[PDB]
Amino acid sequence: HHHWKVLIADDEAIIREGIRESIDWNEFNMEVVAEAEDGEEALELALRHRVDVLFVDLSMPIMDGLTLMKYAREKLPNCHMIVITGYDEFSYAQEAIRLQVDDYLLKPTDPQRLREVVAKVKEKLEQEQ
């Protein structure tokens, strides 16, 4: 049909570049249409592109990751959300459980773990179309 749109939101470029360049997003019928460095730009880019998949760092400047996911679950109610967390605030991901998160991503990440998360999301995405 058409590629599912992915947004990567993270306050460190080295993580956003690492995630985008780690997968053949095309193999999963996906494409990265946007990267964002703060939660405000991310919310705007998520609505601008009507993304289907959001990688979200729990910690973003200006507007933080949790606030972005509350907005994302409201304004893109079918979107699939993957939480990005460093080791030093893994605890905080529990606050996102109520927003229906598909998986949780420790950063930095290796490609086959990533491949696992992305293949899961593609499963759910196919389940509904």
Image (cartoon, helix red, strand yellow):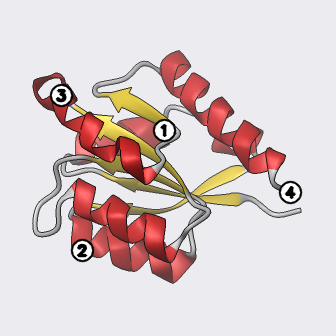
Q: Amino acid at mark 1?
A: Glu
How far apart marks 4 and 1 lie (CA) works out to 27 Å
Task: Give the residue pinned by disc 2.
Answer: 40
Can you tell which quarter of the image residue 65 is in?
bottom left
The structure residue drawn at horizontal position 48% and vertical position 76%, both measured from the top left corner, is: 75
Task: Give the residue pinned by disc 4.
Answer: 129
How far apart marks 2 and 3 lie (CA) works out to 23 Å
The structure residue drawn at horizontal position 27% and vertical position 50%, both measured from the top left corner, is: 10
Q: How many C-alpha atoms fall within 10 Å of the one at disc 1: few (<14), some, or many (≥20)?
A: few
Task: Give the residue pinned by disc 3.
Answer: 91
Q: Which mark is residue 83?
A: none
The structure residue drawn at horizontal position 63% and vertical position 55%, both measured from the top left corner, is: 31
Q: Position of residue 76 (x, y in %)?
A: 53, 71
In the structure shown, which secondary structural element does the residue marked by tag 2 occupy?
helix
The structure residue drawn at horizontal position 38% and vertical position 60%, both measured from the top left corner, is: 35
Q: Nearer the viewer, mark 1 or mark 2?
A: 2
